[PDB]
Length: 124
Length: 121
Ligand SMILES: [Cl-]
Image (cartoon, rainbow over all chains, first blue to last red; front, side):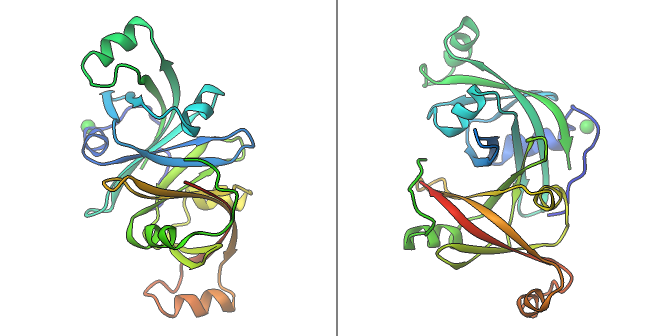
């Protein structure tokens, strides 16, 4: 995998959208001491080239960091090609509002939280 | 995943690092997070890991400015995973780096040693 550079856009290309769609995404947040945290998120989807969404089922450290104001970094990597894309995003969390209810009605996790991610920057 | 109150990997956690793709995360000096895969990650002992920095990209720049380093080794199908928080020591072309890289095709990479501060699972 190559070093990534800032692409000076907040819009994914189609190839990058397909990276996010087709691979297990990893997400990183920042804890209360300013340290990183990282873990996999299987429920990631792409709403449009500047917005992603996932379900927060565990409500663990990532969620607590986000609730405390952390920004979110995401990566989607394709090992066979060694291609990857990363984003920096701000999180918009929907716990039990009508938007959450609408989104979750299409899933089997009615008590999850719906986290939308507004892409600020793309790196590749 | 919860703090285990140790800086030492268990045998199961060593195997998780050995058998799965590891992801690394850092923060820039303003606190914005970064995350990416690290295929060269290796456990040296229960409290130390090591990887190669071949590209010297954003994780590198963040570490240079003092970022601590988070790692995860997840076997997602098996529902097992381990996370660490560590500090880095960067070896660019000292005798240690040379010794390590002699066993690789990457003689100009930097060697980054990670000292585990906390394990989570
Ligand atoms: Cl495109």
